[PDB]
Image (tube, grey):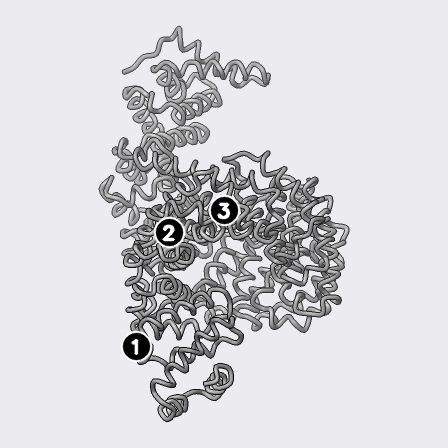
């Protein structure tokens, strides 16, 4: 045995009487002393002892001892002596079925907690033991065992589905299935619960007994007990995902069952049922099985979307479940509408019609939500009703009730495509006017709704906002003074999305006047390692890009923090690479946006960036990122390099030696964006190095020729590849020119399709130079070059004379009669263009 | 990260 010091046990029983004192400040100082005793080891032996052995005590006092012990298992189990432990473990299991339900709960919570903290392979007597106890003839022992087993399957499902314990599932699962039949409804619900853990993992023991499982489920269809029903519903939802086949046969039966449950009095059951419709809808067989029932279903869902009376109360002054019947029904409706398209409206529209206009607001509100939910897939079918509705909704933006104001903002944003595709004055103007008001609404929910809807609307509207710009910024900037936290974040989105939507139009001193100060104000106060510098980078990145050169005043502090972060990150990635156990791996998304913002300033400020580049190790850092193993990073640096190259090649040329070989290796089209931006940045440095490029040409060229001839490459890599070749041959024709016959054809084919611009120009100068040097590359495929030259509408004159000399050079080589015959295989527009423009 | 009553 173990005996406790009776003189010291009367002591503990006092503490336990004081922990139950009403007086707040007694409780305060008594608990700090019970914390104190943890320091010493035997103490926990006194607790399990008060619980399980001292029947001369108050039950609340006993249960409290076990709960205190329990909490000492959560903190401080590494500090448990293995004798205290083993006394506890054994002492729990002898009383797992105590006659007192309060004690039995307490004992049970200990067991599951010890099993959870001090893992299962360290208590391997337990499962075996708990199984054998299910069979117990004593009911309370059975229930106890099963309650524990249940929490264990919940906590430890992956470990049980593992050799760690020698596949103990193979015995228990079939064992559990037996207990679906049991007298008690509690034992029935435990059994189903345990089993449901192992459905989605496709646990072997269960997949092989699937038919027992299903027959057994089906046999509980008609159970009065919510907790049983809840668990049946969970079971059927999961099955649906993994083992569609086995229950397809019985679908209609199942479906009628779920439809009942979806309406169940008890909202737990309801919600669990509702999940069905949602996960059913993602199943390619769905569309047929269900159609018969849409009639009955739609209104069950729609009726589920009203706020309850209690929902409403918690929303006056998030304060409510992030998942509930309302969201679930509503989400189901969105998926349905994307499957059934307009086939859905006959089942909905009439409901809408009387909900939207209904006089009680809760109902009108759910009307609006529905209308929002169906928007995406019922769009076409809704067009005819919108001229009535969109104006109706613009009205409700000023409704007395905020929950009507906010959902209205949302629903309007779902029809933003249509609104923007009309006369701006009928629908868009008054919409945008009311939104802008609501952005400054007194209520936080309405702000978030309104600001988000605005940002959404802005994306669809694009350049149509330029009239209202003045009015928009007034509102957005003023909102900085109101908004905090979650709504502030939506606001940066709103401003970012604005800049992206109008671009340069936003460059005007009066606009930059009001906008920039409060942003750079916010830029500083929020701290590196803050939740919110991520949305603010992306805000400034958008703005900076739209503002162009007008950004300049403001970019020192933005540059510095960007460089800082790129470094700070690589600092950590290093450590983590060498000592991964002690060092937190970094979050690269921080770096990727910084590089993208820096790349944004390089295009934007152009040359004026230069001096900040000089003062910083931006180039070393870039060097490091180009070898980074995540492709998004390599891609964001090559992008940056090409920009820096144009903006200020003088600070770059130093590092070229080192870069070109890295660029060389990254010309691999498996990762397209990197290959693209690498191809691009060698193009751009060609032009700045000119002739001095020639040492480096051997290390890239065969791979570029590789890529352009290599099929199923996206349009705009080839375009960049062609371009870049041209730009090499422009500055080192001697080395590039001999390769001409291999790339001339896909090169022409690819660039005959792009707009007369500066890249086209610089690349075609290239081809012309190489043709002068190896005039026999083109003679095989000369019609391809004719075609590409005829793609120019209005070329620079020098370039026009270059083509002119080539075209006639050839017509003279082959003679008039050969030429005429050659050009008869030209399409009219081309033949005539060349004959008129280059005189040929 | 905008308002969405379906998620």
**Quadrant of the snapshot with the N terminus of chain A:** top left
Q: Which mark is residue A206?
A: none
Image quadrant where one finds the C terminus of chain A: bottom left
Sequence-earlier tag: 2 or 3: 3
From the top left corner, tell me how far across and down residue A57 is, in percent.
Answer: 45, 17
- Chain of the residue on which disc 3 is drawn: A
| Side of A323 where A702 appears, left or right | left
Badges 1 and 2, same chain: yes
Task: Find disc 3 in the rendering and name its residue.
Answer: A598
Q: CA distance from mark 2 to mark 3?
A: 18 Å
Mark toward the start of the polypeptide (3 vs 1): 3
Question: Alpha-carbon distance for marks 3 and 1?
Answer: 45 Å
> How dense is the environment of label 2, judged by Cα within 10 Å: few (below 14), some, or many (20 and up)?
some
- Which residue matches tag 2? A631
Tell me the residue at 45%/67% (across/down).
A286
Q: Determine whether, in the image, residue A297 is placed left or right of residue A284.
A: right
The chain identifier of the residue carrying mark 1 reads A
**Residue labelled with disc 1:** A776
Tell if the residue under mark 2 belongs to the same chain as the one under mark 3: yes
Query: Element under label 3?
Result: helix
Say whether disc 1 or disc 2 marks the residue closer to the N-terminus.
2
Q: Nearer the viewer, mark 2 or mark 3?
A: 3
């Amino acid at each position: 045995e173990w005996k406790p010091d009776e003189q010291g046990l009367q002591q503990i029983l006092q503490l336990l009487k004081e922990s139950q004192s009403p007086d707040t400040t007694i409780q305060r100082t008594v608990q700090q002393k019970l914390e104190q005793l943890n320091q010493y080891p035997d103490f926990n032996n006194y607790l399990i002892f008060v619980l399980t052995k001292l029947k001369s005590e108050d039950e609340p006092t006993r249960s409290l001892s076990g709960l205190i012990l329990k909490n000492n298992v959560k903190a401080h189990f590494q500090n448990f002596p293995n004798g205290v432990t083993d006394f506890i473990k054994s002492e729990c299991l002898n009383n797992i079925g105590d006659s007192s339900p309060l004690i039995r709960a307490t004992v049970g919570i200990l067991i599951t907690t010890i099993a959870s903290k001090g893992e299962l392979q360290n208590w391997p007597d337990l499962l075996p033991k708990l199984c054998s106890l299910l069979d117990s003839e004593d009911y309370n022992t059975c229930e106890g065992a099963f309650g524990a087993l249940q929490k264990i399957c919940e906590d430890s499902a992956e470990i049980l589905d593992s050799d760690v314990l020698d596949r103990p599932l193979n015995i228990m699962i079939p064992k559990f299935l037996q207990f679906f039949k049991h007298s008690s409804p509690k034992i029935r619900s435990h059994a189903v619960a345990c089993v449901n853990q192992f459905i989605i993992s496709r646990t072997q023991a269960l997949m092989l007994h699937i038919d027992s499982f299903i027959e057994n489920l089906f046999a509980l269809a008609g159970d009065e007990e919510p907790e049983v029903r809840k668990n049946v519903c969970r079971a059927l939802v999961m099955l649906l995902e993994v083992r569609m086949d086995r229950l397809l046969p019985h679908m209609h039966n199942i479906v009628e069952y779920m439809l009942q449950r979806t309406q169940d009095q008890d909202e737990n059951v309801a919600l669990e049922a509702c999940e069905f419709w949602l996960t059913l809808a993602e199943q390619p067989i769905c569309k047929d099985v269900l159609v018969r029932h849409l009639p009955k279903l739609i209104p069950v869902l729609v009726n589920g979307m009203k706020y309850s009376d209690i929902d409403i109360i918690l929303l006056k002054g998030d304060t409510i479940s992030d998942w509930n019947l309302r969201k679930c029904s509503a989400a189901a409706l969105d998926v349905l509408a994307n499957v059934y398209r307009d086939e859905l409206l006959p089942h909905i529209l009439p409901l809408l019609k009387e909900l939207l206009f209904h006089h009680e607001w809760v109902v009108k509100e759910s009307g609006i939500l529905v209308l929002g939910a169906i928007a995406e897939g019922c769009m076409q079918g809704m067009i005819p009703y919108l001229p009535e509705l969109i104006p109706h909704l613009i009205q409700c933006l000023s409704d007395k009730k905020a929950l009507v104001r906010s959902i209205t903002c949302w629903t309007l944003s779902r029809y933003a495509h249509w609104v923007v595709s009309q006369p701006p004055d009928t629908y868009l103007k008054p919409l945008m006017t009311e939104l802008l008001k609501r952005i400054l609404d007194s209520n936080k929910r309405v702000q978030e709704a309104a600001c988000s809807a605005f940002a959404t609307l802005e994306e669809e509207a694009c350049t149509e906002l330029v009239p209202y710009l003045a009015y928009i910024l007034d509102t957005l900037v003023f909102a900085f003074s109101k908004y905090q936290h979650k709504n502030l974040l939506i606001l940066y989105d709103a401003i970012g999305t604005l800049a992206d939507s109008v671009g340069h139009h936003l460059n005007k001193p009066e606009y930059i006047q009001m906008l920039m100060p409060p942003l750079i104000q916010k830029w500083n106060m929020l701290k590196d390692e803050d939740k919110d510098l991520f949305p603010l980078l992306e805000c400034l990145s958008s703005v900076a890009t739209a503002l162009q050169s007008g950004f300049l005043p403001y970019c020192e502090p933005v540059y510095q923090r960007c460089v800082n972060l790129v470094q700070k990150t690589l600092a950590q990635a290093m450590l983590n690479n060498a000592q991964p156990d002690q060092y937190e791996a970094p979050d690269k998304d921080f770096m990727i946006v910084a590089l993208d913002l820096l790349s944004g300033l390089a295009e934007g400020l152009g040359g004026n960036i230069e001096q900040l580049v000089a003062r910083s190790n931006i180039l070393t850092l870039m060097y490091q990122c180009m070898q980074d193993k995540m492709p998004e990073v390599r891609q964001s640096s090559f992008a940056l390099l090409g920009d820096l190259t144009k903006a200020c090649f003088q600070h770059v040329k130093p590092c070229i030696a080192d870069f070109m070989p890295i660029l060389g290796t990254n010309l691999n089209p498996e990762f397209i964006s990197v290959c693209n931006n690498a191809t691009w940045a060698i193009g751009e440095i060609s032009i700045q190095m000119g002739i001095e490029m020639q040492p480096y040409i051997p290390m890239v060229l065969h791979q570029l020729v590789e890529i352009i001839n290599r099929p199923n490459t996206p349009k705009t890599l080839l375009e960049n590849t062609a371009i870049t070749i041209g730009r090499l041959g422009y500055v080192c024709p001697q080395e590039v020119a001999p390769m001409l016959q291999q790339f001339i054809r896909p090169w022409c084919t690819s660039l005959r399709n792009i707009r007369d611009n500066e890249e086209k120009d610089s690349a075609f100068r290239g081809i012309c130079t190489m043709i002068s040097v190896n005039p026999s590359g083109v003679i095989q495929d000369f019609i391809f070059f004719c075609d590409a030259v005829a793609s120019w509408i209005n070329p620079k004159d020098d370039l026009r004379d270059m083509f002119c000399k080539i075209l006639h050079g050839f017509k003279n080589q082959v003679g008039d009669e050969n030429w005429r015959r050659f050009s008869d295989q030209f399409p009219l527009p081309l033949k005539e263009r060349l004959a008129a423009f280059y005189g040929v | 990260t905008r308002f969405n009553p379906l998620a």
